[PDB]
Length: 545
DNA sequence: TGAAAGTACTTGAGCTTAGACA
Image (cartoon, rainbow, N blue to C red):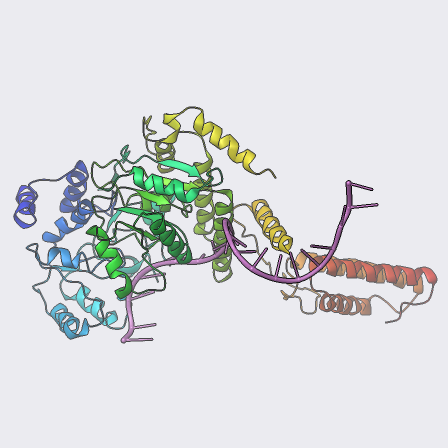
């Protein structure tokens, strides 16, 4: 019975009932069974039980879309001694045991009910017959992806055990539910309810390093103001990770680093011993979306801006898993966003180059621009967060810089504009020029649409891309000009006929295209040849080749 | 009232990036 499994939650895990109406709706719907489940809620125990609890009455075996991508070795070492039958396997040694567990999988009605797997392996040949055998054996229930690394991926399918093996309802217990992302997981992924998180205990404050005379001292006193409880500082490069760690340790704040070309083995410590207060502060770029979301996270600081509002919120959500007031701060500067966008552009570029035009191509751009506006707009931080999520705008108090002083933050914003108007000079000019013209490019660059010649192009080497932005229409218009010039010369010189003039103009256009490299120079040469033809006609002699 | 050229010091920038093969 439903009440019986609700009590079994206590009998298996220990919780008498559901913590929040989140579970009371979502898990109830999963027990009934309606459709795909999309839930956004702060990472931790809750969202994990939102799929683990249905996995108790899994009707045999429940196939996870993917418990995140890594961490797994933390959820498997979270239920093996929780009165449940759970397994995962992926650490290569797996074979030792995995191999026969794959036979324990081949084994019908196994002593296993849960199976952790994620795009990392799975696509491997050890599973291609295994997945078909498992789905054909008796059943294959549920499909939980929890996180967003599906659409938000580096071969993420979005049509994996669903478009390719859809056999049961799906579960999406992510932590980010931006309108574009939720629409993508409704479409690309083929009860749904999100809590307006509010979280007044997280004092979202933004300080501009362009105005701070001593950013290092400011960040130090920010950490010291947060007392001695474990905190997180976010930056964007491993070199930055090392630099901030060294500077903070020299400033006192016991700092550290997560990634640096080091290794799981060469960081497992830094990470774990960060939970147990052995390391007070540790810095990373994106390597802290996992690793046991602990309770006493006193602050989360961003030395450099994030990649988006979704990214910023998902970093800042690795905090406040208590009543601890955790003032999370964002350090901002015009030089920073400048750099981020330039690389978001280079990424979007390469991507489009080795792909086609997708909604994500402009989605990343407008997400970063939304982050820029949020760090540049004037108003409550919680209100901006709700607006970006489309939730009810909260009139928060004592939760953001806007509500503290109604003119100091305005003064800082005004001074930001007044901070900077408008062999060392060459790089400065190049950076300024490219950054400024990236603003002219704006969002969704795209627009390539090289239409092939329609039916009867009179152009030698017509389908050529040696000259960028020289679409076929421009080319045959230039050939049209060349043929007009040839016809004028024919009238002014009284030669045979225009029948050979067609091939003559095609030859001239091909020669000009070969001698040219860019569209403007190609046109310059084309009308230079036209002017030469006109001059020859004016003189009187026939235009010889 | 102009007025000199090389060298020993400091300092302060400044950098894409996260999963699953040995």
